[PDB]
Amino acid sequence: NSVSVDLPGEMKVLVSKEKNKDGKYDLIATVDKLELKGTSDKNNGSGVLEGVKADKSKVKLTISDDLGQTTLEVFKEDGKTLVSKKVTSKDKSSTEEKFNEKGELSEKKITRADKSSTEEKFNEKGELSEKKITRADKSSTEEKFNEKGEVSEKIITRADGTRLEYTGIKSDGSGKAKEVLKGYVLEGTLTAEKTTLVVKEGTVTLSKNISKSGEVSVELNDTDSSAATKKTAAWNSGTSTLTITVNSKKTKDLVFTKENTITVQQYDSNGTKLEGSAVEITKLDEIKNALK
């Protein structure tokens, strides 16, 4: 009967309390819905376990004698050619390799003790195509490499899940840009000094500027002439808020939040106090209608 031994890789193995009829200890484990069975000289839960998938693939879990490391190999039917391989250490660093049909290496993923990771992907002739770095705050950068090994796409993902996406990146540092937010997408441009995302409504255009440092500044420009209608805007970089003025009265704040959202709340008749409560904008129409 059993004794549950936990293992590097977030795995558990069971081992026979007493030796079997051939002298050895039997050990059983399940990993990814598949059951592996093996036997070992040692009583601590080290040794090798094996199993076969319904696609005929052969899976081998090797546990080191000091329990400091596990190796999970998936092989083709021959049991020799590698399909994939994950070595994983007690401090939870690990290496993950996936090989293609000709046996060569198509993806490698390194994970460190702090959950940060790097992940590479190689094309048909061994050359790097993607590189995704993922940080311990769960944020990330995925780069896509063109024929000459220069970055042509980039995709920044933040800890809340929103994304800056940059495409047609070019030698001068210019590109097309896209910001993916909870509910809406802002289109704009990339350049050497900054990212600029544009939102027009009629004769107003609002610009969310994001610099290579990460710094958001927002500006507004109305091109109609009429004190009763023409919208102006002041930015406060301390509180990340655009305050809109029409006819010399504050009409509404746009707050741009840490959480990467936008809110709105209106002033009283005099443009002095803010009223009610702020309201989260979840549609590209809500922002365009706030510019009206």
Image (cartoon, rainbow, N blue to C red):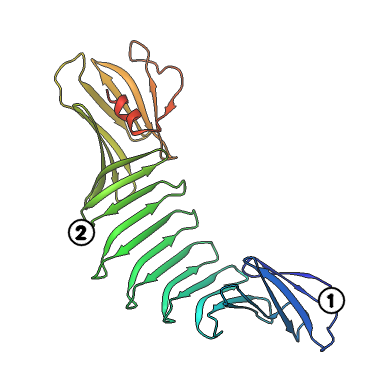
Amino acid on which disc 2 is placed: Lys
Local packing at callout 2 (Cα closer than 10 Å; few below 14, some 14-19, many 20+) is some
Q: Are marks 2 and 1 in contact (CB under 8 Å)?
A: no
* Horizontal side of residue 53 vs 277, given as left or right: right
User: Is the C terminus in the top left, top right, bottom left or bottom right quadrant?
Assistant: top left
Q: Secondary structure at mark 1?
A: loop
Q: Secondary structure at mark 2?
A: loop
Tell me: residue 127, above or below residue 288. Answer: below
Which residue corresponds to mark 1?
17
Q: Position of residue 78 (x, y in %)?
A: 54, 85
Tell me: residue 141, above or below residue 232. Answer: below
Which residue corresponds to mark 2?
170
Amino acid on which disc 1 is placed: Lys
How many numbered discs, if any? 2
User: Is the N terminus in the top left, top right, bottom left or bottom right quadrant?
Assistant: bottom right
Q: Position of residue 197 (x, y in %)?
A: 27, 41
Q: CA distance from mark 2 to mark 1?
A: 64 Å
**Residue that sits furthest to the top in the current view:** 269
Residue at 36% x, 34% y is 240
Given residues 17 and 114, the one toward you in this image is 17
Q: Position of residue 258 (x, y in %)?
A: 43, 39
Residue at 50% x, 57% y is 136
Q: Nearer the viewer, mark 2 or mark 1?
A: 1
Given residues 198 and 135, the one toward you in this image is 198
Residue at 27% x, 42% y is 187
**Residue that sits furthest to the bottom in the current view:** 22
